[PDB]
Image 1 (cartoon, rainbow over the protein chains, first blue to last red):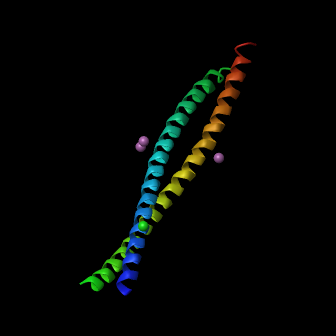
Image 2: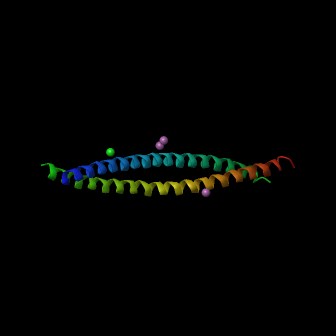
Image 3: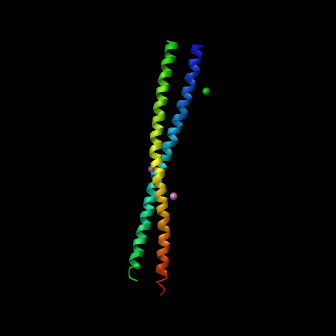
Length: 62
Length: 65
Ligand SMILES: [Cl-]
Ligand SMILES: [Co+2]
Ligand SMILES: [Co+2]
Ligand SMILES: [Co+2]
């Protein structure tokens, strides 16, 4: 009844440990996605600034 | 044995929770930073799209003058 409660508590900690590991696993997933998003956006923005610079020079004429 | 093992294993799993929480909090702090970065790049992307269209039109309105 001490041992019994302790064992039940140990099972509940194990379950909490599994749930925290799943949470960590989800955060790492989302982190890796945002790193990729951030690189995509930078490369997209670089392409746009290049097209703009090109247009700017065209229009520098008149 | 049994009762001392249980007590020890409990203290140990609670130790492990504390560490897993700190780890997840460290991931959240970096993620918050990446959400903020991405939001600024989205705002920039939108302004550049509008500027490109703006400029194309000026050019068209000068490719025809
Ligand atoms: Cl269970
Ligand atoms: Co990826
Ligand atoms: Co990646
Ligand atoms: Co925004």
